[PDB]
Amino acid sequence: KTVVVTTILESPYVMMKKNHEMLEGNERYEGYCVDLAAEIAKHCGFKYKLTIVGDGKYGARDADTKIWNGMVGELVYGKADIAIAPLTITLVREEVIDFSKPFMSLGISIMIKKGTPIESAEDLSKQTEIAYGTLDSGSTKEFFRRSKIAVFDKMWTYMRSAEPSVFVRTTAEGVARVRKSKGKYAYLLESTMNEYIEQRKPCDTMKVGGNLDSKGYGIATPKGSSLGNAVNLAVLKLNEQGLLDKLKNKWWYDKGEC
Amino acid sequence: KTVVVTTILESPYVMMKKNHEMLEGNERYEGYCVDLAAEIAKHCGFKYKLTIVGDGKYGARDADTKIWNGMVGELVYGKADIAIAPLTITLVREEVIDFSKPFMSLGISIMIKKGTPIESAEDLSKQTEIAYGTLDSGSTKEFFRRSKIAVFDKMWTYMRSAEPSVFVRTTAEGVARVRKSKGKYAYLLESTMNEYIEQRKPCDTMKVGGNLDSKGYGIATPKGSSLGNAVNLAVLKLNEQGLLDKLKNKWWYDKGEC
Ligand SMILES: [Zn+2]
Ligand SMILES: [Zn+2]
Ligand SMILES: [Zn+2]
Image (tube, rainbow over all chains, first blue to last red; front, side):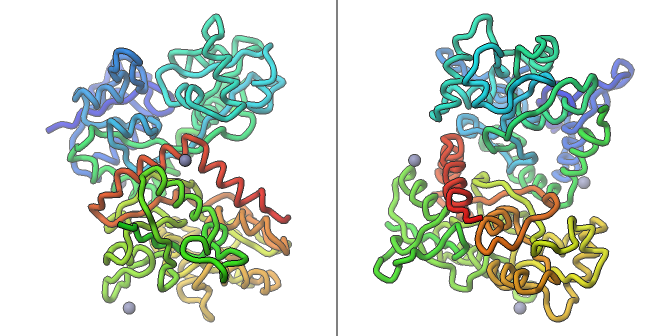
């Protein structure tokens, strides 16, 4: 009956309301994906329950274990009926779960502490003084591990062997590392997140260079799910009506702090 | 058996080669979609025949008869097996045909002759000296027809009644009109085409303002096609391999003459 929605605590997509302690169920959260979930549910005609993914990961398949973790895993193993979050549409994932057409378009980008002598990925690859890494168990790390183009291959070679680890468990951890490393750490993350943080106090980070690739986020459902068709149509309908653009302006710029 | 591919003559997606008269079959054409078709046929392992859509349209539904025209129509009525072209993913089309995840991201944009006093959609809707229109039988015209946002709504009110007609049968017709109108005509087209034309002689046009929306082009197949699933995965694979970006640079800027 009630659709179990798996999501992730990633500002400004999903965040705890300041007074969540005195609220119940779905009312405890706020954000872009919370607003989107309510709309998808309205248009598809179903009641739902928002739940935060247990391991706090987006989703990747363990090499030897072969088990999927994160939100992808919750769907693969039947723990959730749908995932509404900044989950990237990728080949390896579409092989095991279904994705609606994208609700947000983005690409991998570079986040630096203001003043850092870095203007592009090629700049990062040709130097060694400034360390750089990505989020764990996600599409960004896989992008570099599989890239066959010179620059990115060079970047992966370095990142995979760097000590201490240059990878982080959460976006917040990567942003904090940039902010505290005095320009000696650069973070590779999706443009959407980079742009968001660039508008948050202390306004000490910035997105540099063009995006490394072009892709998008999609609402995911277990392969063969009966919700797939309607959800996809809802996303297209909502994008065409301007809701998605309205929602990004609401959570990114209307609330900018810089 | 050989897969019938429907496509449209639209530079730089599909164009007849300089020496096409001495060539046969698929060899007569070149372009982004020609390269994409070859890549997809190779990965999905099938033989194909490129055919140019009979009525030279992308695809819209006749409100009177409810009959689809253009490439969408050739798929809907079984005249073609797959469409590989700059065909926009939209709700009305998704209801009758299948689309792969996008192979290109874009948005509606404004094309002006260099020097015309226009920098945004809002600017066009506040004047009458400068006429403006869109392509017929496509997603762009539908966008304005179905827009409830103030500026675009006013723009449609003007366009749908304009006399002489401000709409055109082909992108080429719209571009030609902008160039010969001494700046009294602005053309609304997707950013992909706008950016392309901006890089071609006589280098007298330019894209102004940001995109009005965000969407993408998808490879289309008839509902319940056996090629659907595979093509979709092929597109994702190609994007992640960097091919799509490779092809974009090859046909847009490596050949740019401005
Ligand atoms: Zn609604
Ligand atoms: Zn290939
Ligand atoms: Zn008619």
